[PDB]
Length: 542
Ligand SMILES: [Mn+2]
Ligand SMILES: [Mn+2]
Image (cartoon, rainbow, N blue to C red; front, side, top):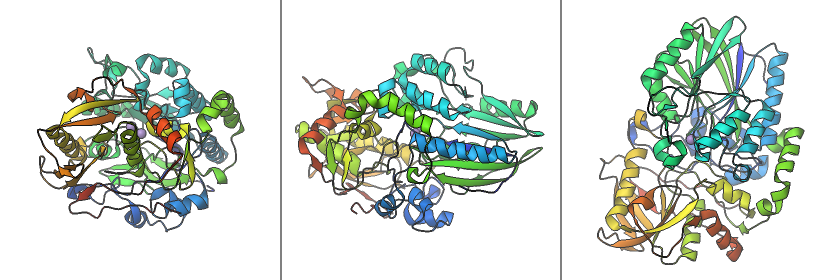
């Protein structure tokens, strides 16, 4: 944390906090499978390879943040990551140092901040905004924020003291932008523009009602125009605070002229060294409060001459307390502490969420659903990248359940699907996740389907990526009707609702199951064989 001065301006960047108020554990994915053309790129590095790529020594605090390798042991060594208190303390420490050097600091939030946590659900996002205000966030962009609905977002923007930016959120009839595209900040004799981009796929990714009247479409012309306008106004350097997803950002760096640095959210990536694409540097925003990225820039009349990037681990056991934040969280959650923090069950093994294809947490959810609804044959779990990690011997609480399943639309649906639909769903998802054109990458993973097994060839043509599907030990029958369960998506829209079943929040089902069993012990049993790749698993004990 004790860095020497560098450059003219400092960006203190974090993204995809997902309302995570408290220190917790968050392991990186064991697999980030890519079609051959995208292999070895930032955003597709895991395990030992990511450590080698960045020259990070095994067993270090950065290694703990960066890879699943040695996870449990390193979690027991360095402690939990994140927490709004610790993140605040770190941001304040860095901002103070910068200002004492005569430098200039900006606090930039990449979005996916307001939602998906106990604190968020209990306050419809308000407490998270109040926290941003305590820290002093200068700008933010968005994605999951919209799951609170337009009206609530508008209310919260009234409360937010920073300036929300987005070049791409426009009225869906007239096309007039609804927010400022960028803000220019003076940096000594220089000027630095921060341009914002919100996720372009909000409409198809969440309930339609949440964004009625709005368009978020990626618009290269409008983005180029914003960049050009900022420079015409005198901006020497341009930074894009983005929620596009890092691969789409990389594609944009080869298409848009004049973007010097992109701060990439959405994909929850980590980039200890910036990724050079075209004439642009790219730095990812990580997630769940794991890290604060410090980017020091040396500017020149026409852009960024050089930069220093440092991933600062947010390790609560190694940072001072932000007393005002601690007090605020206590006041906000005191009335809900018994609910949020009482143990529901103990997990005997590592429960993780992130992976291209499979996770122990998602398997637990599949087992819970099947235990309560034995008629269900396949359980489709949403492959979101937000969540948390439960260590062996650790108690699972309601706060964890909200971290894993805290959608504002948490309903579990039971419906019938024909066999052909099951296969088609996986193939369609595979076509998106494994497209080789980063311009079309959406930044998501593959739905986890408990109750079935399949073979995946990421490099096969569309229509041939998913094969040898089996349900309950038998080959998939295309004309057979199977009872499916799903939450966090739209799959139920193409099925036949189970008569007599009333959809209810997935977290209620999970709490019922966990209270009943008392202890869980999910062993990693991946249900997918991947052609052309070694499918990796972390060590789940220790
Ligand atoms: Mn996110
Ligand atoms: Mn996102």
